[PDB]
Image: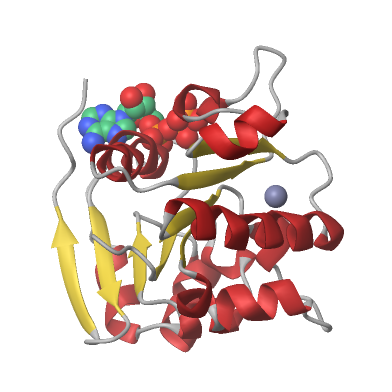
Length: 207
Ligand SMILES: Nc1ncnc2c1ncn2[C@@H]1O[C@H](COP(=O)(O)OP(=O)(O)NP(=O)(O)O)[C@@H](O)[C@H]1O
Ligand SMILES: [Zn+2]
């Protein structure tokens, strides 16, 4: 396993998108000893969602010992992303190919007129660094068009919102926009950007 590609996952709260990352993607990576770093922005007072899936890096010991990492980002900032990304490049040097998992990727991948070098690298030179990406967001138009262009794989859950549907058609695939509308709950459509193919996936087993 050498997960250095870019996967974008679109889905609103309650769609089943988070259950797919949290209870499929993350555990498959863990099972294969593939390191990951989670950029988590949703601070609840009982700590956040992914707190269960990795460790907060504080000490010199953590730096060298902790392969599965959770980062709390209250910054939500280009200055923070530069660090997260430099940090990630180094994490891969230590552990081999790692996956940067960014929940609410809006915070760093939204339309900006001037793109920071770390963002440009993440989008264009991720394979050079040995960092796969999983970029998660609620609505397709949350992210800059160039994300969809640079992705290997785009995963979408059901949406009825017409501006969303129109954006999919304009930036990704007209056919994907037609089929997204037909998705039953917890089903997801996968657009493979390399092969240009669409497949509809059944809901993953849940408890
Ligand atoms: N494949 C599935 N089959 C059956 N139930 C599911 C499935 N996926 C998600 N659910 C359930 O639907 C609800 C919403 O799931 P989901 O959208 O993944 O998370 P969410 O709304 O973002 N909440 P959270 O993960 O707690 O932040 C959860 O109660 C899940 O337990
Ligand atoms: Zn962040």
